[PDB]
Amino acid sequence: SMSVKKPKRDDSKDLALCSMILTEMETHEDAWPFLLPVNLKLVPGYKKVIKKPMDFSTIREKLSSGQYPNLETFALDVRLVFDNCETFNEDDSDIGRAGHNMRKYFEKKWTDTFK
Ligand SMILES: CC(=O)Nc1ccc(O)cc1
């Protein structure tokens, strides 16, 4: 409360560490469905069904231009990529499997790096 503060966690390296994690995501061999925005003109159903599209290149642009206020808003966008993927793709599809794999990959890096 007013003039009563918790000890200050060091957040000065958060931007650099998130960028490192995103680089490792971008270079994973199963990243290919997620590198660029889904083409809303060419993929039936995607625009109407998926209310907030998100992809690695969009996250990279937001990270490089100061659009994440903290490391949690960054994690929310990464998770959104995989939540969208589950919504639109069967678990037993190449893209469905890729999404499950990448989510597992991310959450381990997240825990090891910040928790
Ligand atoms: C990330 C993603 O769901 N991409 C995607 C899914 C189905 C399709 O027909 C084309 C692209």
Image (cartoon, grey):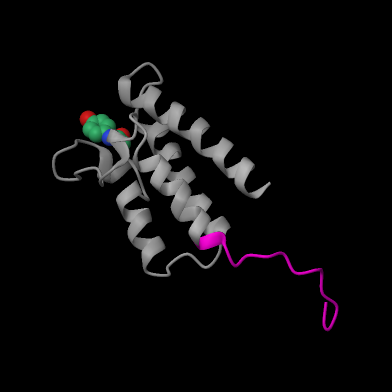
What residue appears at the point 44 percent right and 54 percent down from the top-left corner? 19
What residue appears at the point 33 percent right and 41 percent down from the top-left corner? 49
- Residue 64 picture location, percent across and down: 37, 64
What residue appears at the point 28 percent right and 34 percent down from the top-left corner? 32
Tell me if residue 21 is in the magenta stretch.
no
- Viewed as shown, does residue 12 lie left or right of 115? left
What residue appears at the point 14 percent right and 45 percent down from the top-left corner? 41
Magenta span dominant secondary structure: loop
Q: Which residues are magenta?
A: 1-15
Observer-nearest of 29 and 82:
29
Q: Residue furthest top?
A: 92
Which picture quadrant has residue 2? bottom right
Q: Quadrant of ligand 1?
A: top left
Observer-nearest of 18 and 40:
18
- Residue 30 picture location, percent across and down: 34, 29
Which picture quadrant has residue 81? top left
Tell me if residue 4 is in the magenta stretch.
yes
- Residue 108 picture location, percent across and down: 58, 36
Q: Is residue 55 visible?
A: no
Q: Classify the position of the N terminus by image quarter.
A: bottom right
Establish if 68 lies above or below 33. below
Establish if 84 lies above or below 72. above
- Viewed as shown, does residue 26 lie left or right of 17? left
Establish if 30 lies above or below 9. above
Q: Residue furthest left?
A: 42
Observer-nearest of 51 and 7:
7
Which picture quadrant has residue 43? top left
